[PDB]
Amino acid sequence: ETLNGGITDMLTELANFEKNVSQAIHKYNAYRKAASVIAKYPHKIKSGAEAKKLPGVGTKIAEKIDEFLATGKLRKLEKIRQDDTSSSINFLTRVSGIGPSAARKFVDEGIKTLEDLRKNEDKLNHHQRIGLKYFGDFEKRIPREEMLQMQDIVLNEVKKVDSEYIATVCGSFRRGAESSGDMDVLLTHPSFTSESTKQPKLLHQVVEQLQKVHFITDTLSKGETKFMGVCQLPSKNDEKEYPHRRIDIRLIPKDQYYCGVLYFTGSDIFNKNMRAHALEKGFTINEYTIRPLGVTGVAGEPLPVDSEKDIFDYIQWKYREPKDRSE
DNA sequence: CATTAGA
DNA sequence: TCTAATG
Ligand code: NA
Ligand code: NA
Image (tube, rainbow, N blue to C red; front, side, top):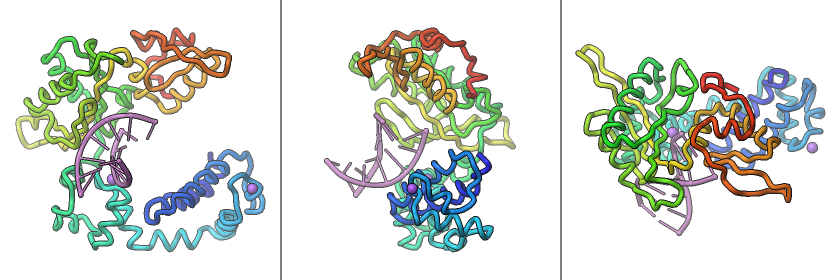
C-alpha cells in the first residue's frame, strides 16, 4: 500500500503503456499481475532478485525493479513520458468515444490535437462528435448540489409519464459523495421483469420525456434497455448556464432492481466485502440476484427481493445506510 | 461483462 | 459479423 508503492506505480505505468500506445496485450497483462503480486508482498522489495522470487516476476520486470531501485527513475519510463506520439494517444483517448484503437488511428493520420480533431470533425462519429463537443464539461466534476437538482427533475418526469416507475440514482451520489462524475439512473417497472418479454417503450417513454422538457440534449446511445446521453440544468435567469453532463438511464426487470441497485451503489469494496460474506452465510450475490449455495460445490435458485433490506436479512447483516456503504 | 454503433 | 467503446 506504500512500502511497495513506486514499484507498483511504475509497473502500472509500464502496463498502461503497452496496452495503449502499443498493442502488447500480453506485456501489458504481464506488468499487471506483477504489479499486483508485488503489491501484496509484505516487505520492502530490496532488489529485483528478491522481487523475482515472485510469481509473474520475471527476468524482464526484475531488471526493471533494480533500475528503479538503484536510480530514482527508469529510462523506458522517461523516454515514453517524453514521446510525443505516445503522449498523443494518451490525450486523444480523453475524448469520449475515443479509445486506443482510434487513438492510434488518428495519430497515424496526424490528428494529434484538440484542434486537429476539430478540423476533421468529419473523421469522427456522432459519439466522438459529441465527446469533442463537450470536452471541457465532460471532464468537469458534478457538485452534489447539482446532483440534487438533476435528481429532482428526473424523478419528476419519471413520475409524470407513469406513476408506476421506480428510479434510483445510484453511484457515489447515492453514497453521500460531495461530487460525482456523471449521473447514474437505474430504472424499473413492475410491468417488466425477468420473463415478461420487454417493453422497450418503457425505456423510450422517459427518454422522450426528459427530452421534451430539455433535460436531455443529446444521444450518445439509445438501446432498448440502456440509454446513454448528455444533459443540462436549465440555465437560470441568465449570466450562468450549466455545463453539459453525461447521463445514463437503464431499464431493469422489477424482479432484479435491489441487487442491481445495491450493487451499482457500491462502493467497490463494500460490495466485494458484502459479497464475500454472503459466501459464508451460504449465498451468492451478483449484479442481478442472490442465490443459496448448495454444498455439491455450487447451487442456484434466486431468492426473492423487494428491498435492499431483503438482501441484508438474507445474509443476516446489519442494514447499512448507503451513506456508510463506503467499505 | 454486457450493451450499442458501425461498417 | 466482428470490433470497438462505455460502464
Ligand atoms: Na518467479
Ligand atoms: Na476516451
